[PDB]
């Protein structure tokens, strides 16, 4: 599924992401835009052999099982394919574990490089939430 901007904002809010660990909703929407262009089916292979999955490009080295990332963990206890679903529940719940891990949203390199320190509220402006 490719979400619209405000559609995704609403879905994120509904699953308890606005201000989760103190990150306002626009942060999550911005990160999703740059990670996946709002596409739940997005995948990206890393040089280390891990893969990033889904709307928030959650990596198999730590968070999910894909069967093909040697030495990895599955701390969200999900198959990585769960992260590709048109329903974002699994991505949201895993993202809450990641952002709680100590480095906040810096876990998402694209958030650090393209959203951090910007007017992230722009991403939810206009939206009926
Ligand atoms: Cl915001
Ligand atoms: Cl497996
Ligand atoms: Cl594996
Ligand atoms: Cl933080
Ligand atoms: Na894994």
Image: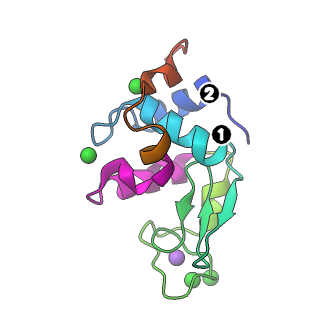
Magenta-drawn stretch contains 106: yes
- Up the image or down, 120 lies above or below 55; here it is above
Left or right: where 44 falls relative to 106: right
Majority secondary structure of magenta residues: helix
- What secondary structure is found at the residue carrying circle 2? helix
Please tell me which residue is depicted at 40% across the width and 38% down the height of the picture. Answer: 17
Question: Which picture quadrant has residue 67?
Answer: bottom right
Residue 13 in the image, given as x and y percentages of width and height: 45, 31
State ligand 1's quadrant.
top left
Asked if the residues shown at circle 1 and circle 2 are in contact, with their CB atoms under 8 angstroms apart, the answer is yes
Tag 1 residue: 38
Instruction: Say few, some or many: other residues with alpha carbon within 10 Å of mark 1 (under 14 / 14 to 19 / 20 or more).
Output: many
Residue 7 higher or lower than 2, as above or below: above
Where residue 108 is drawn, which disc sits there? none
Q: Does the closest atom of ligand 1 sit within 8 Å of the Cβ of label 2?
A: no
Q: Left or right: where does residue 45 sit relative to residue 95?
A: right
Q: Position of residue 56 (x, y in %)?
A: 55, 50
The span shown in magenta is 88-110
Residue under the point 28% across and 43% down = 21
**Residue in the picture at 47% in, 68% down:** 63
In this figure, which residue is indicated by the disc labeled 2? 5
- Residue at figure coordinates x 67%, y 48% from the top left: 40
Where is residue 80? Give x, y as percent: 60, 67
The N terminus - image quarter: top right
Q: Secondary structure at mark 1?
A: loop
């Amino acid at each position: 599924k490719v979400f619209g901007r405000c559609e995704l904002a609403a879905a994120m809010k509904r699953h308890g992401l606005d201000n989760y660990r103190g990150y306002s909703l626009g942060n999550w929407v911005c990160a999703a835009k740059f990670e996946s262009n709002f596409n739940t089916q997005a995948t990206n292979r890393n040089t280390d052999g891990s893969t990033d999955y889904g709307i928030l490009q959650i990596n198999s080295r730590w968070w999910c099982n894909d069967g093909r990332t040697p030495g990895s963990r599955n701390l969200c206890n999900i198959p990585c394919s769960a992260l590709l679903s048109s329903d974002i529940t699994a991505s949201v719940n895993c993202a809450k574990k990641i952002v709680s891990d100590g480095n906040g949203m810096n876990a998402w390199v694209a958030w650090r490089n393209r959203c951090k320190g910007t007017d992230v509220q722009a991403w939810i402006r206009g939206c009926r939430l």
